[PDB]
Length: 115
Length: 153
Ligand SMILES: [Zn+2]
Image (cartoon, rainbow over all chains, first blue to last red; front, side, top):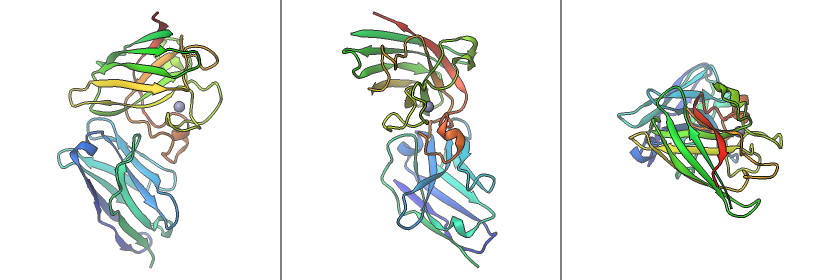
């Protein structure tokens, strides 16, 4: 249903590009978000993309100006371009729908920031 | 058994008709109808405070909030009275609206008659977007179409 990839270890100031393949039924709601999750904590919504065309992205305050969300409608995929990474960004990242009932989480992808 | 109806119109092609029904006083309200001309996917769907159409949907003001709470989804306790969440348009652009909500009413302090129903350009993040605008409008974007809610029966 949801398959994330692209995470890893990156030094402070580095960059990463997380990818997610979602099922066509989930993608066709055109409301997709990336959530980050720290150990023991609840997953917080970090980036959203909705609307028609290429979609329109919104960002939570700790990532605004450093992260960009995008999508590929044909491939039913969502992307999170993370730049200027900081240790506070270390978390397991998941991609899911938002603004409606959450679909079953995928495996996510781990992102660690440390030199 | 109060009944209401709203004719959603706007500048573009989005348009629809949305009916409301409340069998008992202060009980749940059924909201059902059809919107068309939308992009496929989720679209914010709210009751805004004023039934003023003098300057288009912009005149409707903010989400109806007689309790001065923060924005949320219809299932959240912290929510505007007029926070009805998202409606879903199919590939053809037709959103078949079917909603049951106990916070809006057709009488009392939570009465929405004479206020404005508005469908939005993008999805409502239900207040979980992690930014200030998400606590106000849910980042649902511009107003595509709206209409005053009027008495039907
Ligand atoms: Zn609201």
